[PDB]
Each structure stands twice: as C-alpha cells, then as structure tokens.
Amino acid sequence: ASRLLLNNGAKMPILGLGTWKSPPGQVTEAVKVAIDVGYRHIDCAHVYQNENEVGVAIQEKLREQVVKREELFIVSKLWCTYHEKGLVKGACQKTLSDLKLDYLDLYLIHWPTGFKPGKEFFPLDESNGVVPSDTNILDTWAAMEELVDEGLVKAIGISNFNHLQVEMILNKPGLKYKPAVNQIECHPYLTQEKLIQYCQSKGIVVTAYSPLGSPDRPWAKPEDPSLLEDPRIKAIAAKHDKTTAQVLIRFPMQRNLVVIPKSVTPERIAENFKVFDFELSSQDMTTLLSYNRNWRVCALLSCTSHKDYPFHEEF
Ligand SMILES: NC(=O)c1ccc[n+]([C@@H]2O[C@H](COP(=O)([O-])OP(=O)(O)OC[C@H]3O[C@@H](n4cnc5c(N)ncnc54)[C@H](OP(=O)(O)O)[C@@H]3O)[C@@H](O)[C@H]2O)c1
Ligand SMILES: O=C(O)Cc1c(Cl)cccc1Cl
Picture 1 (cartoon, rainbow, N blue to C red):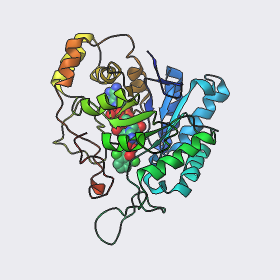
Picture 2 (cartoon, helix red, strand yellow; picture 1 turned 45 degrees about the vertical axis):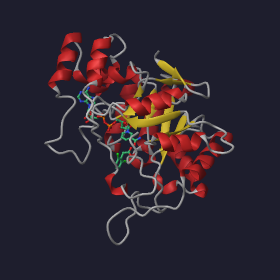
Picture 3 (tube, helix red, strand yellow; picture 1 turned 90 degrees about the vertical axis):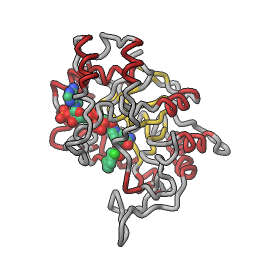
C-alpha cells in the first residue's frame, strides 16, 4: 500500500530515507525536510558516523508535533565489530543514545561477517585483509533475539545475507523470532529475482538499497555504468512524465519491496517522494527486469576470504 505488514504485526512504510554518506553537517536538515515532505521511515547505521545528527532532526520534529513517535519507523544496524554476544546490547544502546530514542522499530545485522572488536570499523592485520571474529551467525542471532525480549527493538532482521545464510537462521534450533526483513542491493542492473522470490516465500520483507545505483559511492569509476543516465530508463521516464530517479524508486515498490533512496538535497528529497501517483505498466516492469547484468555495487571486496562472505553463492 503505502506500508507493508511485517511478521511482528507492525507496518513498515514502503519508502524511506537513506543516510549513508550523508555528512553530519547536512543530514539534520535533510531528515527535517524529509519528515516535513512526508517520509516516515529513516534508514540509519552506527557505521555511517551520523546517528547523533539524524537524532537531532527526529527530536526537533517530535518536539514540534509534526509527527508522533508511533508514526515513525526508524531502522539501524549492528556493525561487524560487535557480533560477539557480549557486545550486541551495548552497540544497540549506543545507537539508541545517538538517535535519542528509547526503542528502534527494526534492528538489522548489517553484514553476516564478524570482525575483530575494537575502535576500527575494518580492523586490518600486518598484511592484506580484514581480521575476522570467530563468531558465527547463529550466536549473533540469539543476541539479537534478546533485544526484542528486553524491549529495545520491535523487530529484528538481516542485511546482505544469501539464501543459505537465511536458511541457517530459519532452521536454528529453538528459533524464537524470524528475521522480519532482509535488506539487500537491488536495482535494474542487479534485479535479485531468486533471492527476492526466496525471501518473499518465507514471509521475509525485502528492502532494496542503492536503488539509484549509489552514484556517490566512494569507489566509483568514470567507466562505471550509470542507472540515472541509461537512455533506456530515460525513455520509460519520459513516457510517464517523471524523472529517471522517480522511475527507479517506483520500480521496487511494484515488486512489493521497501526502497530507501539517499539524498541530502531538499529538491531531490521532495522529488523522490512523488512516486505514489503513477504506475509502471507490466511491459515497463518486464523491460526493467531485462536490464539485469548482475552488477553489484557493494561487494565488500576486502572480505572475500571471510568464512561468512555472502556473495560466493549464486543467491
Ligand atoms: N545494508 C547495507 O549494507 C547498505 C548498503 C548501502 C546502502 N544502504 C542504505 O541504502 C541507502 C541508499 O543507497 P545509497 O546511499 O548507496 O545510494 P542511492 O540511494 O542509490 O543513491 C544516492 C545518490 O543519488 C543521488 N540522488 C538521490 N535522489 C536523486 C534524484 N532524484 N536525482 C538525481 N540524483 C539523486 C544522491 O545525491 P544527493 O544526496 O547529493 O542529493 C546520492 O548521490 C543508503 O544511504 C543506506 O541508507 C544500505
Ligand atoms: O555497509 C554499508 O551500509 C555501507 C558501506 C560502508 Cl559504511 C563502508 C564500506 C562499504 C559500504 Cl557498502
């Protein structure tokens, strides 16, 4: 609709605002603008280094009475250096302090890979490569389940998990809470048909990240393709009197996915909201799906030898 039903009975808004790469100095205004414009879902993470400033915006709009807490859907994620059972609660509480909230609507395991705990987000050894933790996914899931029982979070989920990693959790002896959501990279160049079908069959809601192809990703090359500039996608947009961004945001919505485009620009934040007033035809949808090239923008290349690296499996 405008909201999808999760397995805990809560409704998740189908459109949310992304905050990765949003500078601390600009993200407070961006969130304020988003809330005014009508966004009710914000995607956060400790690793984005801007939760405090996102929290400032949320507090201002709650105090102004523009929104009530219950109408907001706030998401954050447990970083890889906090997968140890004894660290999960502390990480969640830090995020809660920064955002200035008493609960999260949804808390995700950010990546299936655990790293060595410490101050560095990507701890490195003497040579090449990230230092892994010997923790596994099931022990981390058990720690996440405790967060629900303690009232710190309403729902728990996963991000960048392949179907075998999802299976692992679903077959966990004594599984108490199923993952509500799997947040994955998804756009016309990486359509994820198999993983999406798999998750939806298990009652797991899929959130599509990098829906515009993350043009501001720090490792972008000038030779790299651009979704926003694809003349085939421009042509569909022109047919509907919409922008290519609007088409790219509407696309996942019609696949029953939640989508979280990032912007710090008030005019683009507003433009990205205007996606409820048109429909892509079944022809448009089939055509957009045909553009798949299995091109993955977020491949976590420093973790390719990690025992839990998600992207060796087909899906
Ligand atoms: N779970 C995970 O591992 C994971 C990984 C990656 C991302 N995410 C989440 O997904 C969010 C979205 O992905 P993303 O940040 O990679 O990139 P994205 O949303 O695909 O693209 C963001 C870029 O597109 C620009 N943009 C936004 N609206 C536009 C419009 N209407 N017209 C032209 N350009 C527009 C933004 O510019 P301006 O900001 O300058 O306006 C920014 O440079 C993230 O912020 C994060 O919340 C999660
Ligand atoms: O994990 C994320 O959400 C975004 C991210 C970060 Cl913060 C750092 C390196 C790579 C990537 Cl994809």
